[PDB]
Image: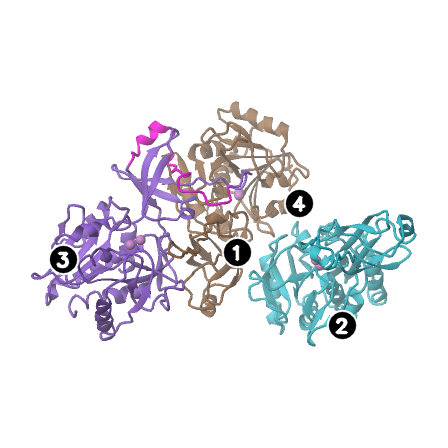
Chain colours: A purple, B brown, C cyan
């Protein structure tokens, strides 16, 4: 119910711009506790209580996938990348081409095997690849897919020891999950200031979902719950299963230091093993230091942004257990 | 029932040496038509009729996987390759570690993402990789896996248009399938000479299953039904769905020319679109020209030996439809 | 008597094709227990008991040396390599040129020292070298050596701590030793099935001694006792002195798995510290999976195929102690 909750949300396709299938399902499991409104741009916003705008929580729906840019003469699909993938993760891998008519499966096979003796033994760049969907010609392809349909990897699900979980799309699905688990566990409790949960769009392509929020939402403290890339010197003693991490500093922003304490305190004062770190990249929260106390805490992750992303199942536990015990005790 | 037959047989793990799980299941669906004997080395042999030994048919159970060679101090698994894989297909991919106690899942994640700035932007070699299984230490790993346990990729299944099929393990599973479909369709027909169906072991590591057969089985004509790697100049006008291919020539052997005719004839004379080709590598049949008329016919395949192998579903149809209409009309 | 037994057998020159001097001496110490026959090709074969052919044991006489291919105008010897040496082990080293007239010593000195200032600071390839034997001219050389005389390194002997031993030619001499020690310890015991000890030729150049055996000797289980190259990831937890190793898998063959157990069992059931491994290269045994249960067990070795090969003296102890306790209790 934590797993299958997770299996349920990684499986949903939807990269930046195209988050529909994800937020429709968030609404399936939210409809009947709390009350939503949907941004223009796309954002699920869900206030709790009324009054001055206190905390804001953001996990983003969109993920990294491929935009279909056009079609070849023999009906293979061209694509650009949306977000940040690594090409070696593109070569010879099933995908899942999402269209209007609905899901449709193909394969970025392109794998000239052992017996061709022009050995392309370097990594083959994202633009030399195409998707196979079994189309016979340029025409037959359009029967099935049009430009600006997008696609995503057929995602395996794996539970490693008993503790960990691997699949592509933890960034930031787990987060979307958390802010649901951690919203059912609120509301009827009510004793508050006034906290705003949000499910952002287009984070992986420039945070644009949260840059849109930054209007109408001037809160006091704005959090992001995205991933925390793990296990490099520069990650200090962060290791997996030693509880949620506070992105103190990344590449998008170095974050409020007093806010850091204010949670770190609530942390130990509340029986939790929060840990602290310095990584790379950025987080929706860093769209708010514009004017706002920002910080984003997260779960440390291995093999990030690959279909092998691996979060520890306890940290997730403790992290909702904290990003709740924040919305009160702050 | 052709698909799910195929889905059923690719899903079974078992690389060279370790074919058990595969032949036990072949026997589950053969037990009660025809009669088997199992080689020393491992081979399923199934005669039909009695008398001089006429034709021999071989599809091999084993596949390409990874042998676990040892364990690291932090409980990651080391492995060698068994067979011929390409390393770019090793990087960051779920696998499935088969042990004695039974199946156990892990991930060759190893994917230093975007934020480490020593960019290993070349392909990372098979020996710098390890499997993650979520073990905490060298000790905790052995609790789960021992050397000479082996592993295989979590295999997706994909049906491309309606026609084609992708998954890792068509080589030579489809073949194992064929020689089953095409053995249920025999026997009770009986009108013969005397044909031997065999399910070989260790083909992908030197044909050693069929090199073992070469004793006790001196037939008249020996066929192999393995893959036919496709879509390179040197493949002539072989294209997918234009019916089974006759490996005229590969790298292991150039095959009987009269036997080629003798089938090519039976082909057109029997309403089939056999095609002919020159590829690379070898086939169990080429363990018999030692003394024996050899030839191996097959289904053309794209993206071979990658988890994206793609055979056309008709060819398979027509190929059983022919490797039957051979066991009589030859 | 284990050492000097070993010192005695490494010292004997004889590479593939030219094993005489070795098997004559094996016969000096075997003549008067058990009874031999010598293959055409060269193999010492020594049955024990009579009846169905049960086990076969092979250690090979030949070693890596140099074939003299011709002679220079100033009476230096040209050579090819027989087997697999590494060139850096050729540069500037005494050798021992075996002729018909008998032993004759020379030196692959060739060592342009410090004062020539064209610095050949890369490794100098096997074909730029010649042997010095002190001959004054092309003519004077032939007075001493003719083509297809061969040569071998002057071999030092070293006993490292008290435990280990270094010298060039453990592969497979130690093995030849074992199957002698372990044949004097049989015979008069007699209680058997029927075991065949063999001393093979030409293993280091394609196993051709044992490929010749494969006729007339169809046994039930065929073992090889050759070296086991040691101390690389891919060698798992094999370390020196932790008892004989079972080559589970190498590059020539992945070996019977049930036979592996059947010894591993007899092992622990018999008070021995057998260990298991995956290395590279091959073994005479792998000439039998042709039709036969093959496996080769061995002693782990460091610095293999160099005049520094280093086996642990206990393992050798325990290995005869086991390859005896096999010839009965199997
Ligand atoms: Co994210
Ligand atoms: Co991300
Ligand atoms: Co195959
Ligand atoms: Co293959
Ligand atoms: Co040897
Ligand atoms: Co050797």
Q: Residue at x 66, y 67 (%)?
A: C329
- Tell which tag, 2 or 3, sits nearer the viewer: 3
Q: Quadrant of the N terminus of chain B?
A: top left
- For mark 2, does the 10 Å Cα neighbourhood hold few (<14), some (14 to 19), or many (20 or more) residues? some
Q: Are marks 2 and 4 on the same chain?
A: no
Instruction: Report ligand 5 position as a quadrant.
Output: bottom right
Query: On the rendered image, what quadrant is the C terminus of chain B found in?
Result: top right
Dot 4 or dot 1: first in sequence order is 1
Q: Which residue is denoted by mark 4 in the rendering?
A: B215
Q: Is residue C200 above or below residue C269?
A: above
Q: CA distance from mark 4 to mark 1?
A: 37 Å
Q: Which residue carries the number 1 mark? A: B127
Please say whether residue A130 is one of the residues in the magenta stretch: yes
Residue wearing tag 2: C3
The residue pinned by badge 3 equals: A218
Where are the magenta residues, as a range? Answer: A120-147
Report whether the residue tagged 1 is closer than 8 Å to ligand 4: no
Residue at image x 66%, y 40%?
Answer: B218
**Is ligand 3 less than 8 Å from the beta carbon at label 4?**
no
User: Are the residues tagged 3 and 4 within 8 Å (C-beta)?
Assistant: no
Determine whether the residue tagged by mark 2 lies in a helix, strand or loop: helix
Viewer-side residue, C254 vs A293: A293
- Eye-nearest disc, 1 or 2: 1
| Ligand 1 within 8 Å, label 3 CB | no
Q: Residue furthest left?
A: A51
Callout 4: SS? loop
**Element on which disc 3 rests:** loop
Percent from the top left, x then y, of residue A138?
36, 28
Residue A91: give x, y in percent of width and height.
Answer: 43, 44
- Around disc 3, counting alpha carbons within 10 Å, would you say few (fewer than 14), some (14 to 19), or many (20 or more)? some
Q: CA distance from mark 1 to mark 3?
A: 52 Å
Marks 2/3: CA distance? 85 Å
């Amino acid at each position: 119910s934590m797993i299958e909750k997770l299996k349920k949300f990684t499986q949903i396709p939807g990269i930046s711009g195209y988050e529909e299938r994800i937020r429709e399902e968030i609404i399936r499991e939210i409809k009947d506790f709390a009350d939503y409104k949907v941004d223009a741009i796309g954002n699920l916003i869900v206030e709790l209580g009324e009054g001055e705008e206190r905390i804001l929580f953001m996990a983003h729906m969109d993920e990294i996938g491929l935009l279909i840019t056009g079609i070849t003469d023999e009906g293979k699909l061209r694509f650009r990348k949306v977000g940040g993938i690594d090409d070696r993760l593109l070569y010879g891998r099933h995908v899942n081409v999402v269209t209007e008519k609905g899901i449709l499966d193909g394969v970025i096979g392109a794998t000239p095997p052992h017996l061709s003796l022009e050995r392309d033994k370097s990594v083959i760049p994202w633009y030399d690849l195409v998707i196979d969907i079994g189309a016979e010609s340029k025409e037959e392809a359009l029967e099935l897919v049009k430009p600006l349909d997008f696609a995503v990897f057929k995602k395996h699900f794996s539970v490693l020891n008993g503790k960990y979980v691997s699949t592509r799309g933890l960034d930031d699905r787990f987060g979307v999950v958390a802010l649901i688990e951690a919203i059912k566990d609120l509301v009827d409790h009510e004793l508050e200031g006034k906290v705003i949960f949000a499910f952002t769009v287009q984070e992986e392509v420039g945070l644009k979902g949260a840059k849109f929020l930054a209007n109408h939402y001037y809160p006091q403290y704005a959090f992001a719950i995205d991933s925390f890339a793990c296990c490099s010197p520069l990650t200090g003693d962060v290791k997996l299963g030693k509880g949620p991490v506070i992105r103190a500093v990344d590449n998008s922003a170095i974050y409020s230091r007093d806010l850091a304490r204010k949670v770190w305190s609530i942390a130990e004062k509340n029986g939790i093993e929060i840990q602290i770190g310095v990584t790379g990249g950025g987080t929706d929260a860093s769209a708010f230091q514009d004017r706002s106390k920002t910080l984003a805490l997260s779960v440390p992750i291995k093999y990030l942004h690959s279909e092998v992303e691996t979060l520890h199942l306890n940290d997730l536990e403790k992290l909702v257990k904290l990003i709740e015990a924040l919305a009160f005790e702050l």
